[PDB]
Amino acid sequence: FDYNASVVSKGLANLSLELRKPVSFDIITADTLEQAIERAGTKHGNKGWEAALSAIEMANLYKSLRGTEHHHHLHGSSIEIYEGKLTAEGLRFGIVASRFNHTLVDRLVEGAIDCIVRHGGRGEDITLVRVPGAWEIPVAADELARKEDIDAVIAFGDL
Amino acid sequence: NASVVSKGLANLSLELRKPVSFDIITADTLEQAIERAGTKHGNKGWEAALSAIEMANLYKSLRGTEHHHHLHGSSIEIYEGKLTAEGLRFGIVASRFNHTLVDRLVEGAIDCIVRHGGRGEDITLVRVPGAWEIPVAADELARKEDIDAVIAFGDLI
C-alpha cells in the first residue's frame, strides 16, 4: 500500500534471481527520535545548498546582463528575458565559515561545496577560509572579495 | 492405564530374571506448554516434507506411460501420488535466523523422509542468513539435475 517500498523490493528480488547474484536490500527504521535528528540534519544541508545556488544564479546574471549576447525569448513573443543559468562552469568561489558551532556550520559548508561541484564547478576553484568567530568575517570576507579571480563570496554565521 | 504396564514389566522381570525398569514423568503447568510447542513444530516440518513427497510422486505418475485406478465407478482417470519416498533426492533450505526453532522443523522433516523409505545420502541441506535469501538459494539447488523436490523453512509472523 506504499507503492514505493513494495515495488523496490519486487524489483531487487527479481534482479537477483535473473542475474544469480546476491542483492542485500536493507532500509532504515526510525521511531519519533531519529526522524527528528534526520530532519534537523537535512534542513541544515538544504540551508547551505540554496545559499550557494543563489550565488551561481546572480554571478551568471551579471555576466549575461552586461554581456553582448542576444538572449532568447519568453515563448517567441520577442520579449527577451534575462535570467541566470544554473551552470557554475568557469566560476570561482570563496567560502568563509566560523569554527564557532562547527558541528553545524560544517554541514552548511559541505552542503554548499557539492552544490558547486555537481553543477559543473571544478574543485580547483573553491577556496575555503575559516575564522574563530563571526566577528572575524568582515575583514576576511573583504580580503577575498578584492581578488580578481573570485566571482562570489559566501559566509556563514553562528547561532 | 499406567499401572498395568508397570505390573506387566514387573512380572516379566521375575520370569526372565533380568532387571527391567519402568519410569514416567509428571508435568507441571509450564513443561506442558514447552512440550506442546516442540510437537507442534515437529508436525509442521513433518507435514511440509510430506507434501513434497506426494507432489514428487505425482509428477512421476502424471508423466508416466501407465494410467491407474479410476474413480468410485470407472471411466474417469485419477492421478495421485503415493507416500513412498524411495529413490527421491531432496533439498532443504533453512534460515539461520531464529535457528533455535527452525532446526526443529528440519529435524522433523528429515525423519519423515527417512521413515518413508528415503536414505539420508539423498538429502542436501543448505542454510541461508535470512528468509530474504531463500528464493535465490533454492533456485541454485533446483539447477542441480540430482534434485526432485525442494523444502524451504522461514521464520516470520
Image (cartoon, coloured by chain):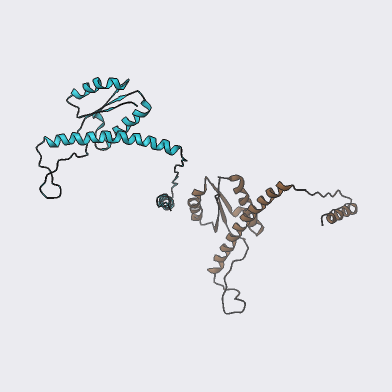
Chain colours: A cyan, B brown
Q: In which quarter of the image is the C terminus of chain A?
A: top left
Q: Residue A140: give x, y in percent of width and height.
A: 25, 21
Residue A97 in the image: above or below residue B88: above
Q: In this view, does B73 lie above or below A86?
A: below
Tally of numbered tags: 0
Question: In this orientation, does residue A5 appear?
Answer: yes
Residue B96 image-quadrant placement: top right
Q: Position of residue B46 (x, y in %)?
A: 63, 56
Query: Which residue: 90% across, 52% down?
Result: B14
- Looking at the image, which residue is at 59% across and 66% down? B81
Could you say where residue B133 lies in the image, as x and y percent from the top left? 49, 48
Q: In this view, does A73 lie to the left or right of B62?
A: left
> Residue B128: percent from the left, percent from the top?
53, 46
User: What residue is at 39 percent from the left and 38 percent from the top?
Assistant: A39
Q: Which of A29 and A74 is in front in this view?
A: A74
The answer to whether B76 is drawn above or below residue B112 in the figure is below
Q: In the rendered view, does B29 fall on the left or right side of A56?
A: right
Q: Nearer the viewer, residue B152 or B101?
A: B101
Does the rendering let one see residue A116? no
Query: Which residue is drawn at the image coordinates 15% and 47% (left, top)?
Result: A74
